[PDB]
Length: 285
Length: 291
Ligand SMILES: [Zn+2]
Ligand SMILES: [Zn+2]
Ligand SMILES: [Zn+2]
Ligand SMILES: [Zn+2]
Image (cartoon, rainbow over all chains, first blue to last red; front, side, top):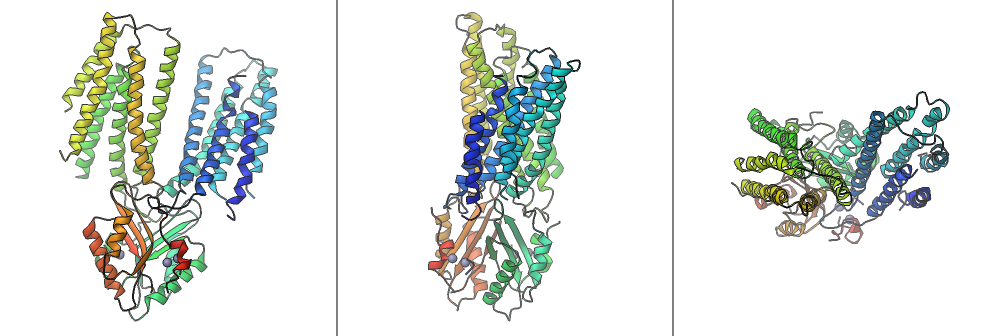
């Protein structure tokens, strides 16, 4: 008949961390004291949207909205990065600037400790929702050390005085290198692309492992947000065989292969027309 | 059975290049000259430029057929680029309102708008020379719409040449134009978001299509009804259905899909055509959409 364990593990992840970065929240230096707080509050928002039920307009529910908000946060990250870059290139163009070289250090003192508390505690031992907040936390950890160490030279030998530019540069660059991966991941998720953890051809062999299947076309198997996969394909079997028990055994095999979320099978007839099935011939791969 | 590219590129890539140099002119008149009002349409021209860009981009993608990792072609990358361009519009409007409210609170500036007027005067004249299916009309309506916006920027600045008394025509006009453009963004982004989360198309109705299902001799009971569209107008269908053992299930779904095609166009569709086991009270995982 084809028919709150791990998501609930996330309630104790940010609801506290939100208040923590809130307490965390020089006047211009306190600017990024909220870029993390807002992001993680929106992450919790995404969690509550994952809690939502299905509907008619949204038959599957309100799930991918989580990735939507995630990528929105990532775009705001893209934003704040370029902001810092503008500051750095301008202050390169304006190499003159005066401020005590430790007043920012002494407040980055708690910051490096502030960030690392929430960052690596949020480290894994696998919803990307958590990971998106983590790489942000891991991201602003760079902001914690972008000026802390890079200003000590000014405090010690200001004959260079511009180590903050290069350190900000490299840290923002590494944040972006962190982004690119999950960026392309989220893309192919929303791009209706099959999940990374799966091998289309592998699933094909899983199918063909049954005596019943003689051919399969119009196969489509993509996933929801994280581990919720949807399956569709056509199949022709021996006309002598009972599709019902056949398809039941098929679904049995697909389940015993690995997890599923939703499966549809056309169960076509052997009849069928290969020479012009080219419309769904095969994925070019 | 379960079922020009050059000119397509050229007449649209070249047209986008015409819009590009349009932007180029209105922006070389833009920054150093005045820096106050003219930049308003700049984005609008630029955002429509990017719209044409991403449409031809999507054609370029469609030139690549689907693959193993991509079962449905590079279509939805259209929406990706669309929403990204939307966010660019949002950030440019944001910096615009930022500087505008700053100049409002900080009146410390001065402008000889006249020399900045004529560089923006022929700009709307350039909007005049650039003038079917109710879409080209909608584009002509868009064109007419662009005028109302573009023509408004001058008439504001003109009396100021005679009336230095107020001088505040630029902030308010920039503000209202930002409102119009952000409202357009709101509309289109609501549309595209509802499209995402694998939403059903607005042009169609779940209840209507499921009634079309239930209105056939074969059907006895359906469930798992999951239907939606890809990017713009290509819809996909998935659902289960049980009926009597006597029915020739194959021809049943055959005629079902036939009547569905008859109802309207689809891109893909699958049906499981389930059995009269029917664990109805335990089908709560597939009982109905909450609506
Ligand atoms: Zn079922
Ligand atoms: Zn075929
Ligand atoms: Zn087929
Ligand atoms: Zn059920």
